[PDB]
C-alpha cells in the first residue's frame, strides 16, 4: 500500500454564538453554500484530515465529537479517528483523520494561549494542534481575537502574542515560533476584523451584499488592509473571498444582517464583516492549493455562518536509507557560499547562524560573521565561505530536494534570535552554485533578509 505524496485537508471555522447546532451540518463538511465551493461529484470522497475550529462553543467535547463523527460518517460512510481535541474556555479545535492514517500520524501536540490582561483576560485566545504526517509537519491554530470595529490594533497584538507563546511542534527548534515550525501551518478562527466603513453606510453595505457586489466592501476589510500594510499575518496566504460577510446575522434565517447597536452588543454597531477566516503558510516550493473557500447558507443557529476551506497539501514519506537515520550519508552535502544577512537592528553585537533541519542529526552553529554598515543605515553581516558544510543524514535526491533549512541569526552577546527564515532545497540543479533568499522575521515581524548562494550535493 503506497504512501501518499498528497493529502486533502478540510479546515472549518464557526463561531456558534453559544447556541447548539442544528440537526444537520453536512453542508459545512461538503464545502457547499457561497464562495468557492466543492463539486457535487466529490461529495462521497473523504478528506484525509478534518480540522474543526469553533468559538463561543457551548457543547462539551463529547457532545461535539459525537456530532462531528456522525456527520462525517453520514457523508462518507467512514468512521474517522480522533487525532486531538483541545478546548480553552469556549474556543475548541478537533482534528479527525481517516483510519488508514492512524499509523502515519505521530508527535501530536496541543496548546493554548490566553490573550489580554485583567479586563481583557478570560475569553479570547487560541488553541492549536500539531503533528507529523509521515515526513511532513502540520500545524493548526484556531484563534478568537478581540471583537469590535475600533480594535484592529488589539487584534494584531493578539496575533503576535499567539504566535510567540503557542508551544507546538519540535521543541528543539528553539529559535523558531510556530510560523517556521511546520511544513504547512493553517491559522483560522473568528479573527474579528471588520469592514471599516461609516455606521451611516449600513443599509448601503446590505444592498451591495444582496447584489453580490463585494469589491468595495473587501477594499475596506481590516484584515486585507492590515496584511497589505504588513501589520499582521506577514507571509501568510488567503484565498480570494467570494462569499457574503459571515457576521452579524439574525439567528434562524440568513435574510437579515443585525448590525444596529443594542445593550446586548455594549451599544456597538456590528456592520457586516468577514470575521471568520482561514489563512495558511507553507514552506517555500511545497505544493499547497486551496480547492474551496466559502460559507454555508443553511446553518443558522448562530449570528455567524460557518466557513470552510479545503487544501491539497504535499507530503513526504518517512525515509530510511542504509546510512541515515542514525548516521550521516557522506555522498550528501549542503554548502552556503557568500551569504550575508541584512538586519534592521541598531545593535552592534557580533552575530552567528544556526541551521536547523530534520535532514541533519542536530542543528549546526556557524562562526561569527563580519559586520559592515549598509549604505542606507543598515547592518550587513557577511559570512564569506566560512560557513560549516552541512552533512545530511540521507543523500538520495528524492529525499534531499524535498527538505528545508531553517536559519536563525543570533547575537553572540545574548544568544537571542534577531531573525528567522527558511530556505528550500528544491533547487533547479545540484553541484551548481544557485542564488538563495529568505526574509528574516522575529516575533512574526520583518527584521531583515538572508541571501547568498547554495551548492547541494546528492547521491545523483
Ligand atoms: C488517532 C489518530 S492518529 C493517532 C496517533 N497514532 C500514533 C501511531 C501509532 C502507531 N504507529 C504510528 C503512529 C491516534
Image (tube, grey):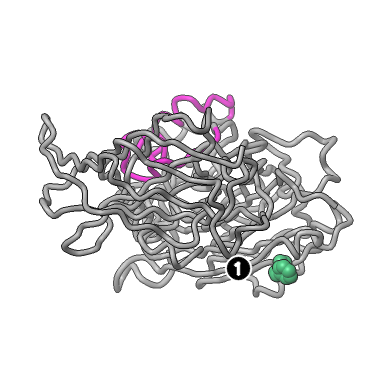
Q: Is residue 235 left or right of residue 257?
A: left
Q: Is residue 289 left or right of residue 39?
A: left
Q: Is residue 258 visible?
A: no
Q: Position of residue 401 (x, y in %)?
A: 57, 40
Q: Residue at x 75, y 47 (%)?
A: 4
User: Which residue does the numbered mark 1 point to in the structure image?
Assistant: 108
- For the record, the magenta segment spans 210-239
Nearest the eye: 16 or 108: 108
Quadrant (top left, top right, bottom left, bottom right) of the C terminus: top right
Q: Residue at x 48, y 54 (%)?
A: 357
**Number of numbered discs visible in the structure rendering:** 1
Q: Is residue 199 magenta?
A: no
In the displayed structure, 251 sits above or below 429; it is: below
Q: Position of residue 333 (x, y in %)?
A: 48, 45
Q: Is residue 225 magenta?
A: yes
Q: Residue at x 51, y 63 (%)?
A: 169
- Tell me the SS state at disc 1: strand
Q: Is residue 441 left or right of residue 144?
A: left
Q: Quadrant of ligand 1?
A: bottom right
Q: Is residue 384 left or right of residue 213?
A: left
Q: Position of residue 417 (x, y in %)?
A: 28, 57
Amino acid at each position: 500500500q503506497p504512501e501518499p505524496d498528497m493529502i486533502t485537508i478540510f479546515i472549518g471555522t464557526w463561531n456558534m454564538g453559544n447556541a447548539p447546532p442544528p440537526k444537520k451540518i453536512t453542508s459545512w463538511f461538503l464545502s457547499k453554500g457561497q464562495g468557492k465551493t466543492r463539486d457535487d461529484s466529490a461529495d462521497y470522497i473523504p478528506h484525509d484530515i478534518y480540522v474543526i475550529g469553533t468559538q463561543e462553543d457551548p457543547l462539551s467535547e463529547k457532545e461535539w465529537l459525537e456530532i462531528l463523527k456522525h456527520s462525517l460518517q453520514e457523508i462518507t460512510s467512514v468512521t474517522f479517528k480522533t487525532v486531538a481535541i483541545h478546548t480553552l474556555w469556549n474556543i475548541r479545535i478537533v482534528v479527525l483523520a481517516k483510519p488508514e492514517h492512524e499509523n502515519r500520524i505521530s508527535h501530536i501536540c496541543t496548546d493554548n494561549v490566553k490573550t489580554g490582561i485583567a479586563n481583557t483576560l478570560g475569553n479570547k485566545g487560541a488553541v492549536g494542534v500539531s503533528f507529523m504526517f509521515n515526513g511532513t509537519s502540520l500545524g493548526f491554530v484556531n484563534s478568537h481575537l478581540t471583537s469590535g470595529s475600533e480594535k484592529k490594533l488589539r487584534r494584531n497584538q493578539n496575533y503576535m502574542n499567539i504566535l510567540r507563546f503557542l508551544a507546538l511542534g519540535d521543541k528543539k527548534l528553539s529559535p523558531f515560533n510556530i510560523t517556521h515550525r511546520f511544513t504547512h501551518l493553517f491559522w483560522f478562527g473568528d479573527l474579528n476584523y471588520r469592514v471599516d466603513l461609516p455606521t451611516w453606510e449600513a443599509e448601503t453595505i446590505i444592498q451591495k451584499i444582496k447584489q453580490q457586489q463585494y469589491a468595495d466592501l473587501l477594499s475596506h476589510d481590516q484584515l486585507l488592509t492590515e496584511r497589505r500594510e504588513q501589520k499582521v499575518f506577514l507571509h501568510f496566504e488567503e484565498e480570494e473571498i467570494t462569499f457574503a460577510p459571515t457576521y452579524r446575522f439574525e439567528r434562524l434565517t440568513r435574510d437579515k444582517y443585525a448590525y444596529t447597536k443594542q445593550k446586548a452588543t455594549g451599544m456597538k454597531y456590528n456592520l457586516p464583516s468577514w470575521c471568520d477566516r482561514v489563512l495558511w503558510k507553507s514552506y517555500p516550493l511545497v505544493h499547497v492549493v486551496c480547492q474551496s473557500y466559502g460559507s454555508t447558507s443553511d446553518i443558522m443557529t448562530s449570528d455567524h455562518s460557518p466557513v470552510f476551506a479545503t487544501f491539497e497539501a504535499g507530503v513526504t514519506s518517512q525515509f530510511v536509507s542504509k546510512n541515515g537515520p542514525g548516521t550521516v550519508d557522506s555522498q550528501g552535502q549542503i554548502e552556503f557560499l557568500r551569504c550575508y544577512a541584512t538586519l534592521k537592528t541598531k545593535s552592534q553585537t557580533k552575530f552567528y547562524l544556526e541551521f536547523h533541519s530534520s535532514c541533519l542529526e542536530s542543528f549546526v552553529k556557524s562562526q561569527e560573521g563580519e559586520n559592515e554598515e549598509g549604505s542606507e543605515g543598515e547592518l550587513v553581516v557577511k559570512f564569506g565561505e566560512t560557513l560549516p558544510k552541512l552533512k545530511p543524514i540521507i543523500s538520495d535526491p528524492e529525499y534531499l530536494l524535498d527538505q528545508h533549512i531553517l536559519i536563525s541569526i543570533k547575537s553572540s552577546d545574548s544568544d537571542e534570535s534577531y531573525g528567522e527564515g527558511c530556505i528550500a532545497l528544491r533547487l533547479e540543479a545540484t553541484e551548481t552554485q544557485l542564488p538563495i533568499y529568505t526574509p528574516l522575521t522575529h516575533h512574526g515581524e520583518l527584521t531583515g533578509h538572508f541571501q547568498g548562494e547554495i551548492k547541494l550535493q546528492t547521491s545523483q
